[PDB]
Amino acid sequence: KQAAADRRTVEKTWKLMDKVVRLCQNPKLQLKNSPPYILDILPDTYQHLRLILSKYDDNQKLAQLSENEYFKIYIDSLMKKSKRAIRLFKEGKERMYEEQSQDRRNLTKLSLIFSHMLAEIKAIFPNGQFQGDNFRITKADAAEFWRKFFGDKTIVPWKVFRQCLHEVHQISSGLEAMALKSTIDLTCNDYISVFEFDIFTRLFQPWGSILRNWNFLAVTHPGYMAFLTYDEVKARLQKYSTKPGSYIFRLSCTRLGQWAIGYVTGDGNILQTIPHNKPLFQALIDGSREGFYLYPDGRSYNPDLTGLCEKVTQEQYELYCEMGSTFQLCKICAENDKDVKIEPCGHLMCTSCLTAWQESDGQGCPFCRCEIKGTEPIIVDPFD
Ligand SMILES: C[C@H](c1cnn(C)c1)n1cc(C(F)(F)F)cc(-c2cccc([C@]3(c4nncn4C)C[C@@H](C)C3)c2)c1=O
Ligand code: NA
Ligand SMILES: [Zn+2]
Ligand SMILES: [Zn+2]
């Protein structure tokens, strides 16, 4: 339950973003001017919020804006993420100045979130005006699914989204659902907006086999680099410059919904291409046949992707989840947050799953089977 996004609440988020910008302006951070660049994103987020307030220019327009379901979630999420970034610097202390620390890794996770939030608000409020009900999902087959299960909703909880997705494309496990949440819930707010749904379905189209496409292109493909920057992708392929056909593919934080495929040419150069509005596996199979994409990340083995034209381990889902912000979510159900701690082992889950386990005569802890000596209610943050 979020509070009304009135002017006072929007202004609180500006002040919090201003503290995050100042913390990030510290030269001891040695912060790269490379995407997602939080020092450009936060001022741009403030300017978009100003543009929205300029369109809802009277008390009755402001009232309509304050109770808009998506806007309430957006303002509440912006506030929480800004507060989280402030907390990260506070606890991180000197670890924020070490480029390889978990604290700095968490700042990168927040910078990605702020970038995705900015792209989302610009798509949902283009030119400051709410167009969530008139938002056009790019792929028609994906759009039909959204309309079937969610009607004209601009945003739905992850819990509801995942249950409805499972009706069409089966999710085989709790770790698979956790990996999928970190892929679709780009804003890390436990909701799926029509914009996040559009991004996911563009990236892993065609809809008819979307989870198979995602599992094989992102979860287990050696060429997949997530939002790794262009400079890092070029530097990574530089070690394979004498092996033409070595290639990697990445998601672009400035061009959400598009892939960029970097590759080594016959003359040792590293070039890139942005495939059109088509399946990434199609561009990869075509490129394999024409001799352009042969060695994913320089590896001799290029996975056969032709199966997608007409098996993932729990360990593979676990490693994929590291980059996400899902540590606070119960691993058994992947739909409720962890709210109970088992003693003495210390494992965490939601009470609903612990109750189901206890009522099944499950021996000890569901994870380690150690005797449950007691429990304690707890609240978990993704960075614990
Ligand atoms: C590599 C790239 C990057 C960005 N800047 N730099 C220098 C490197 N990166 C780095 C981080 C981290 F942890 F903060 F470092 C987190 C992500 C990241 C965060 C959330 C979701 C994901 C996806 C993902 N891809 N593989 C696993 N996940 C979970 C891609 C999305 C659709 C789901 C990636 C990421 O992409
Ligand atoms: Na989200
Ligand atoms: Zn649970
Ligand atoms: Zn345990």
Image: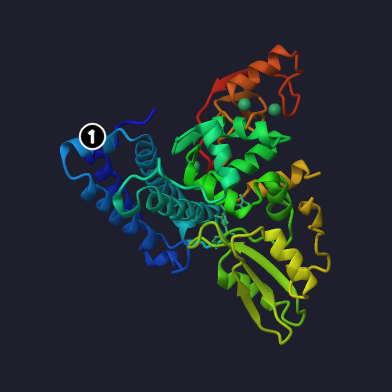
Residue type of the residue flagged with mark 1:
Ala
Left-right relation of 210 to 76: right
The image quarter in which residue 240 lies:
bottom right
At which x and y percent is residue 162?
A: 60, 34
At a point 70% along the width and 85% down the height, the residue shown is 268
Q: Residues within 10 Å of mark 1 (few under 14, many from 20)?
A: some
**Residue of label 1:** 63
At a point 66% along the width and 50% down the height, the residue shown is 206
Extreme residue toward the bottom, this view: 267
Answer yes or no: is residue 377 visible: yes
In the rendered image of this protein, does residue 21 appear above or below residue 333?
below
Left-right relation of 301 to 110: right
Quadrant location, the C terminus? top right
Front residue (pair 49, 332):
49
In the rendered image of this protein, does residue 317 appear above or below residue 98?
above
The image quarter in which residue 235 lies:
bottom right
At which x and y percent is residue 194?
A: 48, 43
Left-right relation of 170 to 113: right
In the rendered image of this protein, does residue 153 appear above or below residue 306?
above
At a point 46% along the width and 52% down the height, the residue shown is 116
At which x and y percent is residue 193?
A: 47, 41
